[PDB]
């Protein structure tokens, strides 16, 4: 019987050819301002171009390389400087190098025995993240997304309060109440439903005109929950909301939590990266008082999806106690290394991706200093965009940004001066969808839009890509004016 | 203000050099029988070799490339033909090509707007997987591991029966009962605890001498739950257990489920890939009767961690209804189907390999793994000092090595206790030599035995001979 792994003359030839296409088309053309951010195709046309159906007979190297080219060609270039659609943008070359190594090594982040380098590396990465929060002791894990990080935090808080629920379930326990801002309630609600608490267990707290949770309303809602028979157990503050980029007042919220004996979770998936900035880290003042912090380096630090940590001040092996399986004890296992290093008991996953190397390698190249410089420059470019938009006709700022989320309407010539008509906001709301379609079909830029509060669709420009220059901000304004002129 | 992304000349030089190191050290040396499966280092020594501390100042390209070399050198080679430690092994070069492309395109599998190729590609992959289960329509998702797929299945079954739980929570429901085999993955219990049901809601059903759930005991446990006023709602059958590789009797289990109106989930994380084999797919006969199927192509098909699908017969958007909070059809977007928000692209690595291989190529590999597993069993029987746990149903070959000092001593009163200590010593020896890695574990009433998983597409008969010869050599003085 022959090896079915592949002709090894073919393997080197294949990977060399593929990496050539990746360098030319994904890494170089995909980050070049002279190329398109996206090549729009209607779903049915793209199906035709991709010939997707999986079938009986295989294909040749030539056929495979043509498919690789097509996949890259028609994919959105998220590393492109004019990709502003998400809370990630850019292609850090060291993070990419780390990703490529990780994929080549294909292991599970599980035991020192199958992942010795990564068991040690993850520990260091989590220790460093904890240091930036303000903790020199604690624990933590990587999770497959911040949404799941948030769920872990809720599960851990529930377990600390009611450890028997791990065996008996929560059905006979009192009603549990958790609290979060109106500006960040989606994964919290999804998580509450998944964990068996129900979305009704989530009490949504008022946010002020800057998008910040109101501590007086938090206190009010805690009292109302108690009056309805519930047991408050957790408050989830948000340090960097997804739309406005607002930062909750952590010191005041920590005070409320302390008064009521509640677990404080900080959802810093987006804003946590600001801890690298000496100039801007004050936005998270009080975060060291948290019981848990979610932080996604795959967002502002550009580590690559997914890179999402849950950080704890805990030193009681709460993760292992809460998530661990019951061990058998009939026969001694004589493991020849310190199995305290292993993380299988800390997670509800079994197999787990290595997410630490892409972050670690980039952090080795950049240092704290390089990552700080990038954060600070993003803040500068966001403020530059705001200042420049005020000088042009048509741009209406939603609010002054606290972070790098710049939110605004584009008012086209046909609506300029018509602010006091009865259907103005209704008409203005239809503008961003049309402009988005045009920029996408042109391939020149992508900006996200959404409605929020009592107002209709406005743009959210996220200023995150380390490649950005002032000229890119100028381009964005110039292009909106050009695409919007006939609206 | 300058770009802070990097000088393009420096970037190309870095990436070409990293790729060279990866090809030389991870892909070539990491899959060569002339090289070590692992280079064992004690944690303290490895910490010194890696200089991990994250610091204020950055480093040069030369320094970064040195670190890349060290990371690869001291990592375990899971593509190596003598890596037998897990339910994945081998390095498929098309899957790897797909992985690299995926990482270079770094997007979220969330909307057609930011992932147009991958939205369409994932639709095809899920269609194909459903087709192989036996469904021409249905739904499904990729999940960050089979453990999470299993949890989704439980959440979905709960929601289908008691949709108001999504808002009102478990306190407002009757006690719920779910059922799984004694041989099942510990993820069902972890999942039950996470979902708020408690591990006590999981009724563990007896398995027979072949490691298969006993349908008569499933029925008995359902009746006992009902007698207590618990509401049965889900049975989780296992098609390919992690230790023995046993396959539950799905037709008989589906009959019990049908009689009681229960959701049938099949945990085929491991065994689901056998659906590609005409010869062996009968091991999953009845799977088309399931409501949900978990299947991990990252295990037997070698797609790359993680590649874990949850497949549903449902066509009524149960996923979006259960988990949910334009110039194209928003039906293409998948964000409402998951409790994740951002989601990795996992389909391309599988799809590209499947394009290269076809069903035919993947089938040939599955069939060859069964042939090599049977070869290993037959050869082991011919040597002194191997005791088979059972005849394998799959590619999990489980056995003790009995060293010369214990041969003939089976009737001694402390034989099993002494024998149990052998696998740990052999494991330490093979790891420190760097020649092979085989997992061991105890089971039932007896102690540590080896589980050799025959999955790597590069395996030959000579590798199976090597394994036996090496255990004999390493165990001679025990
Ligand atoms: C992104 C984000 C999340 C969810 O993170 P995922 O990794 O996409 O699951 C949760 N909360 C906030 C504030 C976020 O910015
Ligand atoms: C692997 C496996 C699982 C868990 O899958 P992960 O992807 O490691 O979370 C569950 N059940 C069975 C039978 C498995 O083989």
Image (cartoon, coloured by chain):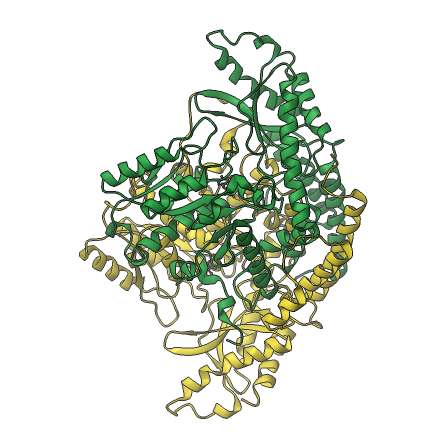
Chain colours: A yellow, B green
Q: Residue at x 42, y 23 (%)?
A: A329
- Judging depth in this view, the residue of A467 and A169 nearest the camera is A169
Q: Position of residue A16 (x, y in %)?
A: 78, 52
Q: On the picture, is A416 further left or further right than A248?
A: right
Query: Is the residue A429 above or below the residue B204 in the image?
Result: below
Query: Is the residue A20 above or below the residue B259 in the image?
Result: below
Q: Position of residue A18 (x, y in %)?
A: 74, 55
Q: On the picture, is B318 further left or further right than A297?
A: left
Q: Residue at x 65, y 55 (%)?
A: A55
Q: Residue at x 19, y 53 (%)?
A: A229
Query: Is the residue A286 above or below the residue A344 in the image?
Result: below
Q: Position of residue A110 (x, y in %)?
A: 53, 38
- Judging depth in this view, the residue of B142 and B126 nearest the camera is B126
Q: Is residue A61 visible?
A: yes
- Residue at the right extreme of this rendering: A9
Q: Residue at x 57, y 57 (%)?
A: A301
The quadrant where residue B85 appears: top right
- Judging depth in this view, the residue of A337 and B402 nearest the camera is B402
Quarter that holds the N terminus of chain A: top right
Q: Position of residue A409 (x, y in %)?
A: 48, 80
Q: On the picture, is B263 further left or further right than A478?
A: left
């Amino acid at each position: 019987l022959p090896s079915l792994a592949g002709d090894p003359v073919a393997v080197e030839a294949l990977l060399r050819a593929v990496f050539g296409v990746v360098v030319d088309e994904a890494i170089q053309k995909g980050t070049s301002v002279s190329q398109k951010v996206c090549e729009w195709k209607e779903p049915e046309e793209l199906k035709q171009l991709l010939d997707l159906e999986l079938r009986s007979q295989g294909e040749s190297q030539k056929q495979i390389l043509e498919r690789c080219r097509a996949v890259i060609r028609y994919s959105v270039k998220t590393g492109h400087p004019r990709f502003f659609n998400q809370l990630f943008s850019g292609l850090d070359p060291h993070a990419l190098a780390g990703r490529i190594i990780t994929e080549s090594l294909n292991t599970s982040q599980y035991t020192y025995e199958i992942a010795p380098v990564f068991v040690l590396m993850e520990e260091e990465v989590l220790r460093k993240l904890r240091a930036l929060v303000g903790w020199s002791s604690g624990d933590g894990i990587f999770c497959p997304g911040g949404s799941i990080s948030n769920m872990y935090a809720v599960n851990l808080a529930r377990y600390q309060r009611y450890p028997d629920c791990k065996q008996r379930g929560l059905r006979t326990l009192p009603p549990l109440a958790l609290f979060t801002s109106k500006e960040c309630h989606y994964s919290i609600q999804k998580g509450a439903a998944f964990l068996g608490l129900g979305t009704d267990s989530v009490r949504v707290v008022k946010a002020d005109e800057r998008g910040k949770m109101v501590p007086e309303d938090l206190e009010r809602q805690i009292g109302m929950a108690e009056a309805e028979g519930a047991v408050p157990f957790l408050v989830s503050a948000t340090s960097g909301t997804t739309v406005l980029g607002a930062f909750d007042p952590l010191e005041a919220i920590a005070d409320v939590c302390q008064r009521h004996g509640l677990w404080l979770h900080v959802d810093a998936a987006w804003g946590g990266s600001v801890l690298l900035s000496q100039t801007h880290r004050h936005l998270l003042d009080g975060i060291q008082r948290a019981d848990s912090v979610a932080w996604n380096p795959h967002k502002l630090l550009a580590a690559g999806l997914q890179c999402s940590a849950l950080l704890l001040q805990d030193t009681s092996n709460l993760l292992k106690r809460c998530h661990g399986s019951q061990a058998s004890y009939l026969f001694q296992q004589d493991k020849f290394y310190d199995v305290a290093l292993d993380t299988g008991d800390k997670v509800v996953q079994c197999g787990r991706r290595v997410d630490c190397l892409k972050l670690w390698l980039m952090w080795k190249a950049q240092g704290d200093q390089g990552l700080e410089r990038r954060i600070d420059q993003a803040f500068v470019l966001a403020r530059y965009l705001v200042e420049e938009m005020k000088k042009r006709e048509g741009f209406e700022l939603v609010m002054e940004p606290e972070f790098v989320n710049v939110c605004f309407w584009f008012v086209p010539p046909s609506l300029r001066g018509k602010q006091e008509s009865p259907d103005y906001h209704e008409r203005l709301s239809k503008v961003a969808p049309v402009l988005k379609e045009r920029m996408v079909k042109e391939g020149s830029m992508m900006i996200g839009y959404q409605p929020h509060g009592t107002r209709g669709n406005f743009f959210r420009v996220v200023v995150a890509n380390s490649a950005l220059t002032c000229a890119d901000m100028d381009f964005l304004l110039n292009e909106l004016e050009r695409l919007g002129q006939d609206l």
